[PDB]
Image 1 (tube, rainbow, N blue to C red):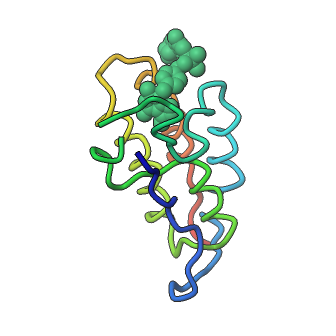
Image 2: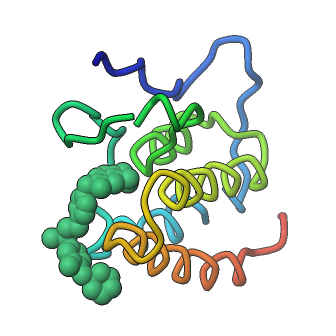
Image 3: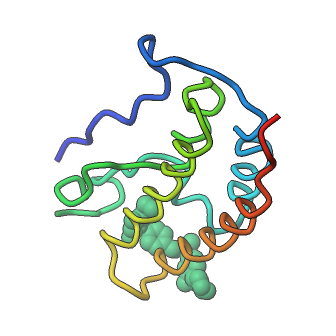
Length: 126
Ligand SMILES: CCn1cnc2c1c(=O)[nH]c(=O)n2CC1CCC(CNS(=O)(=O)c2ccc(OC3CCOCC3)c(F)c2)CC1
């Protein structure tokens, strides 16, 4: 099958801004990205190349760390809640598509545990 176009990372009609919490790029994203389990989550799923049939019939809100990184770099998010939701969509997609206890699920759970540790230390708005 064909892959869908990836999620937008910038939009000329959506207001842009930078906040000190959007920490999410320099601390949270970077800490997850360097983890040895991060690589399957760093780019959109290519369903044919990864042999994942049926993926985009099941997952209609795909999300990956590469998209989140680029959204942050482009000032796409207005607030931390929008960015956190994308991380959580990424984890949830993995838990929905794959079977419980699969290696990829255990990898996502380890990244999610680390994510929550970093979110716990999200700074107050300046
Ligand atoms: C997220 C989108 N996405 C991308 N690829 C996807 C998916 C998707 O949604 N489902 C998919 O199936 N795939 C294909 C996969 C399936 C599996 C996979 C792991 N291979 S691995 O990095 O060599 C590896 C690592 C850790 C291991 O064990 C530890 C032991 C302690 O707990 C944690 C697990 C281990 F045994 C093997 C890599 C791609």
